Structures are given as C-alpha cells and as structure tokens.
Amino acid sequence: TRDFNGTWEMESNENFEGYMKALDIDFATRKIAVRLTFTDVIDQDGDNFKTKATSTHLNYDVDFTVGVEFDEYTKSLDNRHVKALVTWEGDVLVCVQKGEKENRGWKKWIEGDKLYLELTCGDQVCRQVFKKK
Amino acid sequence: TRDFNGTWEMESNENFEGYMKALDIDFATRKIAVRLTFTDVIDQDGDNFKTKATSTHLNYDVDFTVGVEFDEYTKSLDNRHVKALVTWEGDVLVCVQKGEKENRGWKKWIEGDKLYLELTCGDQVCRQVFKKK
Image 1: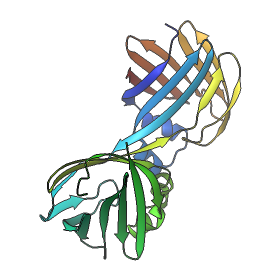
Image 2: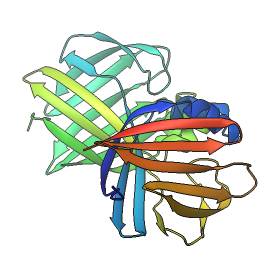
Image 3: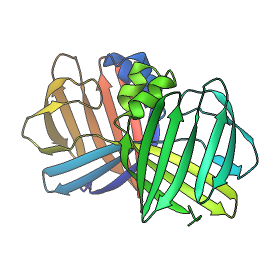
Image 4: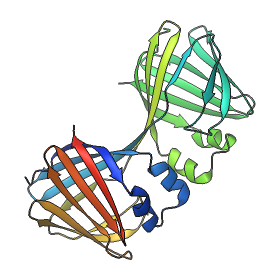
C-alpha cells in the first residue's frame, strides 16, 4: 500500500541516541529525548502529505492518602527525596513537601470546569490551570 | 467539590521557569520544559488518590508533495535548515535532506499494521516502529 494515513504510535526506537549525537544535539537534550514516545499523524491525499509529530513522556504515578505522609522522589523534576503530606483545607488539597528546599509544596482545587495547581518553592510560585477533557 | 476525578489538560502555566530554577533544574532542561503541555489523570476514591501526569510537545507541521523539494527547519531536533526531497521507491517514501550533514535523510514504509521509519545521519541509523491506533 501507498496509503500512510492514520495516527501512528511509537512502539520501538533503536539508536535514537547515536542519531541525535550525529546531529550534534547536546547531552542534556539527548538524556530527555531518549525517554520520549512519539505519535505521528499523517494526512495523505495522493502525493500530498500533511504530517505532525508529537512527543510524550509519562511521569511516575503519585498515589497517596490524604493525611498520611509518604515518600516522594521527584524523578521528573529535580530528582529529590521529600516527605509529602497532603491535607484538606476546605475543598483545597494542600501538600507540604518536607525536604531540603524551604516552603516547597503545592495546592490543588477545582473551580468550575478547571483544576488549579499552585506549585511553590522558596519565593517562587508557579500557577497552572487545567481544563477537563 | 472535593471530586478531583478526571483527565485534566493544561491550559495555562505561569512562572514554571522560576519554579524550576528554584529547584536547580539545569538550563537545557528548563528550555525544553517551558514548551511542554501537561495532562494530569486523577483517580480518586474518598481520601485515596492515584495520579499520573504526562507531558507532551507538538513538533511543527511537515507538509510536502512527493517529488517537490521543500525547505525544512528541524526545530524540534538540531534546528538546522535542510532542503528535503521526498520520492517514491515502490511503496517506500525516501527523503534526502540536503544540507551540511552528509547522507542525512529518512525512509518510511508500512508492513501490516506497522509504520517503519529509518532515520540516517552520517554513519548512524535510527530505526523506529509505530503501530496504527
């Protein structure tokens, strides 16, 4: 068949590292890229092609019970060990991540169709908003 | 509501950079991370939470006509300008990426339910296999 139409999900990727090193992609970027899975979307009409690729990475599961302190290794971020405790403040989930870093933690809550996430470390606050799919 | 169940897709992310720098995440990783979108999957039963986050990045569209050379900027890889020409070899798509790098290009073909992609640069070959979703 000459029909490449479809959404194609990567199953295997051999020697991406060598290919990226031949392209002079730096070490820090290769370290991240070898962990990605790719999805290629191909729209083909005869000899005309429209293609788009996306890369995705699964972070690790975080399972917890509110009120029960648990160990977390932040492998997708700074790869540090913290003792995380999640508590309710009303309908807001409040996590303190006890460890080296001061005032590290997060807050999560729902307003309307949106999930709000405030991540804190030191004097820095990151605010994220998610929409329900 | 205390019900966080659902698949939540990031719409907004403010000051991720400052938060990551507070965490001592290196420049090359921050450069990639500020371009990601996150999807959080939350399975909640009372006070028991199971959560998984994934990050995704859209590469740029590549649209082309077989037999018509086009300019490509490899922004998601080495960020180089190449002159790409895609030709048919039977049912195999063969691309030569004319530029600085020698013997740079790729081949794409389908066998059964699987898409095969061979990426070449210099003496390095990367072989990828995709399954149709």
